[PDB]
Image (cartoon, rainbow, N blue to C red; front, side):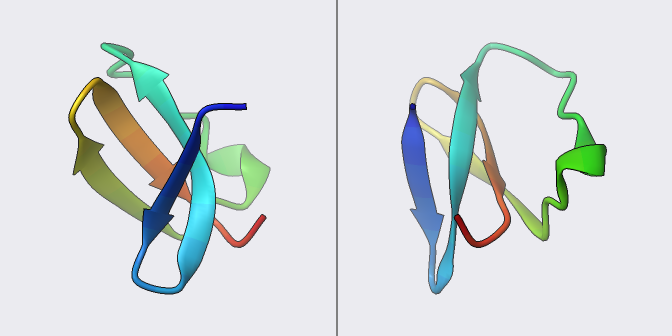
Length: 42
């Protein structure tokens, strides 16, 4: 998986995908170099 971390939140970042499915319990959303970083705590 495309791992991404925001402080303490750990999740997955999507490549150029402006559509982050928040139904996966995503807590935060950060800008990762290659796309949208959707971070819950995985």
